[PDB]
Length: 98
Length: 147
Length: 50
Image 1 (tube, chains in turn red, orange, blue):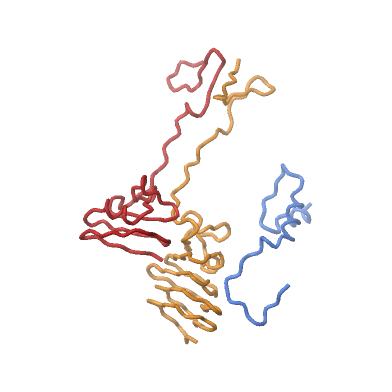
Image 2 (tube, rainbow over the protein chains, first blue to last red):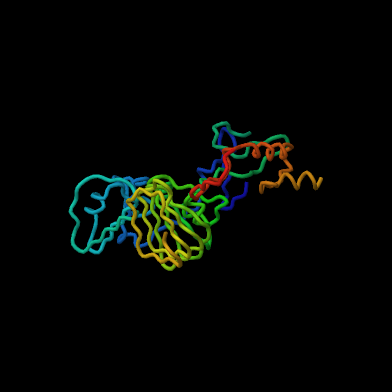
């Protein structure tokens, strides 16, 4: 088996073994824009305790996003239902689409 | 000697050795959001043949998406030109972005309610018969007579 | 051969040289009512039911 560094093949006492787990998959291109300025909130696919508001992991509760909000942050909410009171910060915007 | 642990891709069939074939890639999908709640319409890239309302297979015509709409869904359009008559379903919405042109008539069906429209240039009549109220039109133009 | 294959793609379906039931599939879809396209306009009094 070739001594080149990039070789993937490997051997063991059981035999010549290989699974993709040892093969590196190139990482995908994460999509984001206005990432820290635009806090998306979605009932369908949100997860508050692990969401950052980005399209990759949008919030699920408006209140959670608002607390994390900052000056100039825009809190965008997609159609659906929500619950919980809150109090928006200064210099902020909210836009309930649909 | 080939291992049995299952961490293997070189299982050799008849013939000297297997080499390797299609391996189990992860297929990292693109972002999903409001998948079956909000729908997308476009002319540049949409294709109603296999459209789903997702950002990657948006509907190519307005009439197509409206047919598949469910109560509470939201139809979001993109700039371009679109043709075909239709009638929005009850408890739904339609939203526009930038310049938009529609070639057809729009009718509010019998007993419909909860509709909402905005930001569209309708190139035809707009009939309202058998409706049950609770409607709201905004930033719209009509080339003919509302009836 | 043309009169067969030409009918197989009657519903925009690729020919499959690995399967020997292609024409079968096309016939099945024909009866299926579940696959008809959903309408998107208000019905008129002069539209027929089946």
